[PDB]
Image: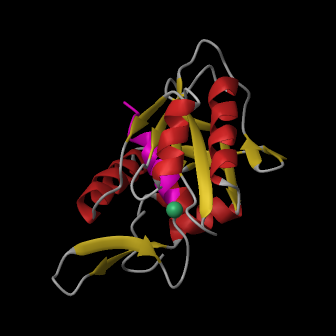
Amino acid sequence: PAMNSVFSGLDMLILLPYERRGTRLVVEDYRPDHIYCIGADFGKNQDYSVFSVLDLDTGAIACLERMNGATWSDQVARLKALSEDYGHAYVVADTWGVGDAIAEELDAQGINYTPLPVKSSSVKEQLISNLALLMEKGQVAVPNDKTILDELRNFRYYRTASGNQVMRAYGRGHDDIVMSLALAYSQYE
Ligand SMILES: [Mn+2]
């Protein structure tokens, strides 16, 4: 890792085998004795949407769905399906800048969700520092997928012109997986 890497506790990340079923990485099927939530980062234009199903009883990701270019309505429909598959799991939705259609459709489709708008660097810092702490404590468990692990590895610290800390992907990379995971783990106790 670089000097400015955010996830200094990557060595304590638990790596889980999975089956790739289309856009889903399935670690395990629904356990009805457990309670789940889903961290949801939507894709605005050609950005990736990522939905991370977290078993709140074990702290392990059960399923992660990722794609780009899906229509807004299809993103909501895929989220509905995931929620229903995991016992009407509640969605932690980053509602910031998603547009009226997704917001309206979450309600119109009766999706079980709570808003967590990632509306500033301060909110992002809260989410990320919680994920990083849980990770160092050996409480984060994710599909053992190189794309996921690489996005975590390449998440780094930078300073703005005003001196404020920001966190983002190295180079010209993506962080939708990082954010989806952080949205899920925001609920984990
Ligand atoms: Mn994103």
Tell me where the magenta segment starts and ends, as one range.
178-189
* Percent coordinates x, y for residue 22 in the rendering: 83, 49
* Percent coordinates x, y for residue 116 in the rendering: 36, 44
Horizontal side of 161 relative to 2 (left or right) equals left
Picture residue at 64% right of the left edge, 14% below the top: 32
Picture residue at 30% right of the left edge, 72% below the top: 166
Colouring scheme, one of rainbow, by chain, secondary structure, one colour: secondary structure
**Residue 15 visible in this rendered orientation of the protein:** no
- Of residues 18 and 161, the one nearer the viewer is 161
Q: Quadrant of residue 176?
A: bottom right
Q: Residue furthest left?
A: 162
User: What secondary structure is the magenta-colored segment mainly?
Assistant: helix
Magenta run includes residue 184: yes
Picture residue at 47% right of the left edge, 55% below the top: 99
Magenta run includes residue 15: no
Name above or below for residue 171 compared with residue 164. Answer: below
Quarter placement of the C terminus: top left
Picture residue at 27% right of the left edge, 62% below the top: 120
Q: Residue furthest top?
A: 33
**Residue 153 visible in this rendered orientation of the protein:** yes
Horizontal side of 90 relative to 30 (left or right) equals left
Horizontal side of 132 relative to 31 (left or right) equals left
Horizontal side of 62 relative to 54 (left or right) equals right
Name above or below for residue 100 compared with residue 153. Answer: above
- Of residues 86 and 56, the one nearer the viewer is 86
* Percent coordinates x, y for residue 187 in the rendering: 39, 34
- Of residues 116 and 70, the one nearer the viewer is 70
* Percent coordinates x, y for residue 38 in the rendering: 54, 37
